[PDB]
Image (spheres, coloured by chain):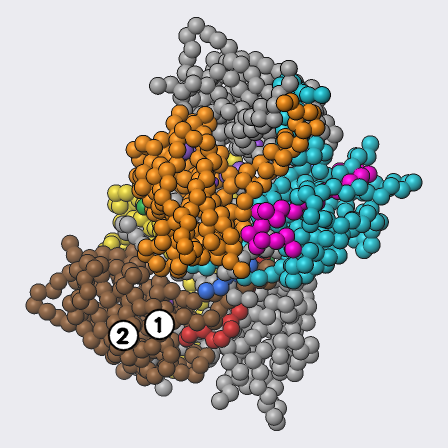
Chain colours: A cyan, B orange, E brown, F yellow, G blue, H red, K purple, L green
Amino acid sequence: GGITEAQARAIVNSALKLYSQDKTGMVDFALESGGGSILSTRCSETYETKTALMSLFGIPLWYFSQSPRVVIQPDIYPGNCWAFKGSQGYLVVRLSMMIHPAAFTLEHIPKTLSPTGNISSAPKDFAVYGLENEYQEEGQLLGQFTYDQDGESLQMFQALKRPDDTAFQIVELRIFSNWGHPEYTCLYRFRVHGEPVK
Amino acid sequence: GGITEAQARAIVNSALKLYSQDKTGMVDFALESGGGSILSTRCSETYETKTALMSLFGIPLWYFSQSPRVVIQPDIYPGNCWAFKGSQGYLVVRLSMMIHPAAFTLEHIPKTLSPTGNISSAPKDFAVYGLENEYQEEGQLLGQFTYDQDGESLQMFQALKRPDDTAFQIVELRIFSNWGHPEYTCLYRFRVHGEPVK
Amino acid sequence: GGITEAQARAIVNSALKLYSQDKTGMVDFALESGGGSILSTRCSETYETKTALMSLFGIPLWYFSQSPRVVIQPDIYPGNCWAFKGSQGYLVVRLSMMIHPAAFTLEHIPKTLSPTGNISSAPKDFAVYGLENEYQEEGQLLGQFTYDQDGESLQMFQALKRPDDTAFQIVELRIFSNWGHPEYTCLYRFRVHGEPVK
Amino acid sequence: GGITEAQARAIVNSALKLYSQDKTGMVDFALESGGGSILSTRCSETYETKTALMSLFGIPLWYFSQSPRVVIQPDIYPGNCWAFKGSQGYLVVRLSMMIHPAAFTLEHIPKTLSPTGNISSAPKDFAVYGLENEYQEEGQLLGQFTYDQDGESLQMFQALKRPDDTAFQIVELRIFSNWGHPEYTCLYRFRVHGEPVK
Amino acid sequence: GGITEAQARAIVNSALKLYSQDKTGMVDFALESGGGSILSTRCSETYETKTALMSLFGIPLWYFSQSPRVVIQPDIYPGNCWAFKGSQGYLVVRLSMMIHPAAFTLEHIPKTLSPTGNISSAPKDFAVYGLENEYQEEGQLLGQFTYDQDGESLQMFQALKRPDDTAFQIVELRIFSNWGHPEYTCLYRFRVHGEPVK
Amino acid sequence: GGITEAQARAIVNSALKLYSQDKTGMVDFALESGGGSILSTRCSETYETKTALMSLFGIPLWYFSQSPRVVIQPDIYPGNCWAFKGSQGYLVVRLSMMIHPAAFTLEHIPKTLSPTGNISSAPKDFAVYGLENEYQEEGQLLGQFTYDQDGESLQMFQALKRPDDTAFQIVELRIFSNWGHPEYTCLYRFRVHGEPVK
Amino acid sequence: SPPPTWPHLQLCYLQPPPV
Amino acid sequence: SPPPTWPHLQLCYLQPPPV
Amino acid sequence: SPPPTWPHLQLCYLQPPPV
Amino acid sequence: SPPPTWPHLQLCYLQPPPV
Amino acid sequence: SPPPTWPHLQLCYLQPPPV
Amino acid sequence: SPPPTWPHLQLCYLQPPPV
Ligand SMILES: [K+]
Ligand SMILES: [K+]
Ligand SMILES: [K+]
Ligand SMILES: [K+]
Ligand SMILES: [K+]
Ligand SMILES: [K+]
């Protein structure tokens, strides 16, 4: 019934190895440093306000806000997120390889770390689509899902299984609602997983 | 007396979850990305030397030194610290919310990672104060403490309990001594924890 | 034979403490933020292609590729690596202190995270040399080794033991082969460990 | 019949005084430094070629071509002219005051200074119009004229006299032909003269 | 009584030679390109308004106004002048050599070229002082004068003759009144003439 | 014997017309704005000193000195000249057209405008050569001359006449001596005149 | 005083980067 | 190698400059 | 040769950033 | 939108320039 | 259109940085 | 303090400019 010291050490070491591999141990074909990129003309407008002012030698120089690129970068400290106006928005990503998409990951900060006391800005209902080229207006539905505010920070979602699985190198994320924030919605990180084409 | 494999897995997973939440699982109201900021005209002078030279196309372009902003950023690799001259100094931070402060965190690198073989540049005796506005010269004492060079990298400190707990959005960190370095003192990260006002 | 809950908690906590200390618990005298630097005129040419284009206000502005400096920076997400042309190359590093070198670390991404499906760009056979000054053409051999593509992401290598151990502040890494990639070789992180001179 | 030394000195001094007053002694309400400006979205495209390359530290940095702003700047050395593609083009200018326009000036270099041996790039047939606002598509004709390649460098043109003289603060210059250059037309300086409104 | 063709040609050629020598044929020890400079902390504030907006790729980038440096630069097209608020102001210049000052020149545009129809912004009553060092508050009076709005564009003024003529390398120009403009005063060019010290 | 008023006016107007045509009425195939350029790797080193310091927001930013490009730009106010170390130097220019060179112009400031009281920095003995390509070490002599410090500001020099006149698009100016300045020689403007090839 | 907004620096790949 | 084209710096007046 | 010192780029918040 | 004001670039001479 | 290549910003230490 | 020296911006023509 009980475990030995050697067995406990092996369990710990295996868990830290998986943690070190981007928490999941799975390729992220959206990650910017590995070859993913944002298709900027196909994203929602950024939530525009006068919040962050950058100065040099004491005089106002320019305002700063996060761009959609941060959604395909791994830092998820509070504020390292892209914000769009309201509760409906979209983001289009070009992947580092042509793949058969199998699953998607969304991360948000946990409530225990939020400096507003809530994660009401998190996405709630969303869907993912595959696009055959950068000009296609309506892509193929790959799945519809809900990010659970009472679940874990990192949540994974399985793509629909079809008889003929088409390959894609462009994916659209569409947000339909948030967890109640009345001004904006915040996206920390979106990942795309699957099998490369031969 | 002994634990099962399932119990060991649960202990490991809970420890990694806490580790992933900024090591503490507690909001840091000083963190810059979440809305904290340095009040620059209320900090000590930076330790000024000709150490780091940045070049472009082969010709000297400008010298680099870390600014006080790094004290409210999470990277704590050796050198990712703000240095001030001597062993007395101060830093003033504006918080992301008005709060009742309850505790403070200081981090320094461990001796096992120092490329000088010591952490004599670490802070030793220090205190924390609350300021009602950015022009107030003497704030209210929130506690006096000592960072222990023989303790852990991350150390937490509990604020004084008073009968009437005043709320603050500005905090001063004052260093009174270091662990022996004869030229400067280095600060890696300072955090502020507490309860937001309604 | 079996372990208690307290014993399991202590094993977990010790493993996370070591993980938090740059995975190894050992000083890295090559790390740039702590005082290491690349001697640029003594590195191989960078693999030069038109891959990454940076724009501002819609118009092409400049191409981006990683520099040899990333080899002495800790982020090892896919693509955060220096690439040189072919399968023979070299990198020269100035260390943060004069030391007796004892060991070296090389990291590469695991195959499970590669967006090409392979780590054929990883280094295979390599050697390390100590240089007495920045103009010396042939340094003293400190060891010859092979990075194992079927091993762990982080691999450590022990320096040769000699009767008279000379101290060095400059080290050359020479790559003799890779794991099969026909165009380039990629280096994620190189570390240098040892005992400082008194 | 003959003139005295005093009379000759007075003639010389008067001619140099007029020369010093922008050659004409008349206000130019298009001049940029005095408050004129180009309405950029209402000009022809600039003749686009790879001619002038600017470098810094030896590496190509960016190409340079003259903008339409030079047409309302006084330097008329060879090449200090705006070039548009072909022999039909247009330029829209906002004036420094609301005026009744009375006359217009065009300058081109003389043939004796051209490094191509000709002034075939000079404008030939042109017209000038007054616009009531920056969005008006067709303005009021103020005159149609021909720049004479066998005339002087600076040529003046009188506006049409109407019974009710409308005031304008925006003027369009339209070029209908050039003196034979098969690729582009070059404009050195355009001026607008008249009476300010009370 | 009358002059010959050869005599007229000689008069013309002599007048153009003098014109070509900065109109005066006299060294200007204030001229910036020859070694004069503005002592910026000893000038009046610049007339501050939102007039000139510079853009790049369509978005507002920064406002432009002329600095006091233009007063020691030779271009005097309308607008190439420094403006200060009101009708009292001052400018301090360091000269290219230590000299005995003998005379001063002020230029303003002629009324015939002003796009406002007046030169009411021109200086009227002014004085010039010599300063022994850059920190001296009250210098020695070198003369008090009036710029005549009904005179010529370029006007010269003779310094006071004293029994012991002190040498100076720093000069203050003080304006006491203007020709009526209710918001600002404009200075086009100030020159300083004299004999260098051995 | 004497001239009429009409005749005097015609003499004045003709002299001002010639003055307005770059003083000479002749094409300058070296002029930068018209298509001439400096071949930078074939010029002498620039006289290097710490003279002119440019600042922004109060802090030293960079030193300024004139480049060889100013020798093919028309402004000749004091200081708008290229300086090289000592009294022997050279400058290589690419012309705007392939020509048969016929004459050369050198300008220097007159002594009456020098803020040092002398033109001892002016060139004295010099020669001009034609080069068939940018790598040719020794070109064909086009003439040897002396700039006269007791002559006029602008001096012209006639090229040697040969039985077979070769055409050139690259010219070297070589200075062999100056008028006595012990540290440097200054060049204000160099021009190249001739007949374009068909 | 107010400054402008820093446009978002944009990044695109003409071919995959080395990994 | 080729660089980009320097966009034309643009200048506009919200009100007349001092003259 | 010596260059100048890179002034510390400064950051302030007129209101809280999105989180 | 509004940008900032271009500070006046300043020029000083540690010794006389060549003339 | 094509731009140039961003030269690699280079970093060297005249003496050790504070740690 | 001392800054660096402003390299001379260089200008070359791949073909003649419009005149
Ligand atoms: K992120
Ligand atoms: K830090
Ligand atoms: K790395
Ligand atoms: K022009
Ligand atoms: K001026
Ligand atoms: K010049």
Could you say whether the residue bearing mark 1 is in a helix, strand or loop? strand
Q: Quadrant of residue A194?
A: top right
Q: Nearer the viewer, residue F140 or A14?
A: A14
Instruction: Say whether disc 1 or disc 2 marks the residue closer to the N-terminus.
Output: 1
Chain part drawn in magenta: A97-121
The residue that label 1 is drawn on is E84
Does residue E179 appear anywhere in the picture?
A: yes
Q: Which mark is residue E175?
A: 2
- As drawn, the residue found furthest toward the right would be A163
C-alpha span from label 1 to label 2: 10 Å
- Tell me, yes or no, whether the highlighted magenta stretch contains residue G14: no
Disc 2: which chain? E
Q: Amino acid at mark 2?
A: Ile
Q: Measuring from the top left, give residue E49's x and y in whole percent.
A: 44, 71
* Front position in the image: E71 or B65: B65
Query: Is the C-beta separation of discs 1 and 2 under 8 Å?
Result: yes
Q: At 46% across and 64% down in the image, what residue appears?
A: G1
Quadrant for the N terminus of chain A in the image:
top right
Q: Residue E138 location, x and y as percent?
A: 18, 67
Placement of the C terminus of chain A among the 4 image quadrants: top right
Q: Is residue K13 left or right of residue G19?
A: left
The answer to whether residue F191 shows anywhere in this view is no
Q: Quadrant of residue E193?
A: bottom left
What amino acid does circle 1 point to? Phe
